[PDB]
Length: 143
Length: 200
Ligand SMILES: *[C@@H]1O[C@H](CO)[C@@H](O[C@@H]2O[C@H](CO)[C@@H](O[C@@H]3O[C@H](CO)[C@@H](O)[C@H](O)[C@@H]3O)[C@H](O)[C@H]2NC(C)=O)[C@H](O)[C@H]1NC(C)=O
Ligand SMILES: *[C@@H]1O[C@H](CO)[C@@H](O)[C@H](O)[C@H]1NC(C)=O
Ligand SMILES: *[C@@H]1O[C@H](CO)[C@@H](O)[C@H](O)[C@H]1NC(C)=O
Image 1 (cartoon, protein in one colour):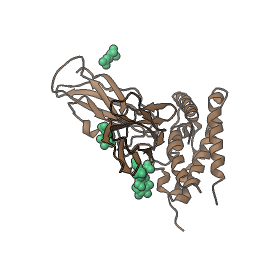
Image 2: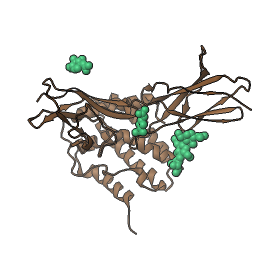
Image 3: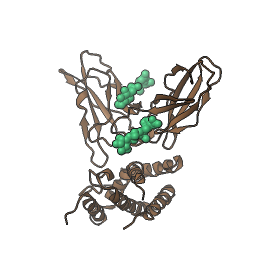
Image 4: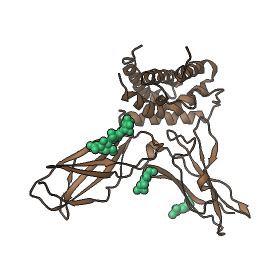
């Protein structure tokens, strides 16, 4: 699980991002993460795939947010996120469609349709649920 | 109407509550209305059905519809009578994962031969995020100077104690919860459960 120090450093970054958002517009035209997003709604085999997609999007957005003003407070959080992503990718073994396909589609479209403010607010507010809830469900069925 | 005073969002036993005090102006049989913020990405103040027009000075704020316990949120209360509605008073933000206060577990005791097992159980709010709860069992002879403390153990696992056949004294167990997110939070020790040890 995540150590107190990793979690303290995520909180500091999450709070700094929330602060910076008070001073920009970050309206979203569609929810970046679907409102019912929850890995427990997916088959065990599908969960790592969903988790990977939110993790990769989270990393890409926070790296682009990591300008000179925030690079210091985002450095530990990005390092931790990279390491989780690598551990996860190492364990991912590769006609109507269901929630997994719909959710990945929403994630994949978000960076093309939405403002940077929208993507930042969305991965920022999704961050602790990602770290504490989604990461936990996947680690039950690890493979 | 004078707005409610000292409006406070706090946590107890894994749950969240809003409390307050009556307005400066002190009319009577006045009632209160309560609302909470939903998730930051779809925010809207929503009313708490069960607290609507309450005459109480608190309100449970746990497992509310559309509540997002993984982000900060505030509650709000206003004083109301037929003759007026007060302005809204907001609480500070409360950020559940970092501010929740754990309760002690309720220990389930079983015995087999010389092994006494003390197993933590909890009644948890159904919406609770999956916290990593651990617990620390204390064990002692009633009235004794020192107590023994067993290793901190994860919820899910019992603590195992070896009994001394000949020690037929009244003994006592208690436990507290340790919840660690970024900083360890300790509950109080539960009320001691006591018993006469007897091996054969
Ligand atoms: C000590 O008490 C704890 C409870 O505080 C017991 O752990 C719990 O054990 C039950 C019984 O197996 C588990 O229940 C089931 O959960 C699984 C997982 O979702 C589900 O598939 C089943 O349908 C059922 O609902 C429960 O998960 C578990 N809780 C934990 C580990 O946190 C434990 O069995 C006790 N140990 C003893 C008596 O030695
Ligand atoms: C009540 O609120 C007032 C105003 O903030 C504060 O000065 C006082 O310390 C509070 N006392 C209690 C008991 O809440
Ligand atoms: C704590 O919360 C649970 C779950 O809502 C409840 O069932 C239990 O009675 C509570 N315990 C105490 C000490 O009030």
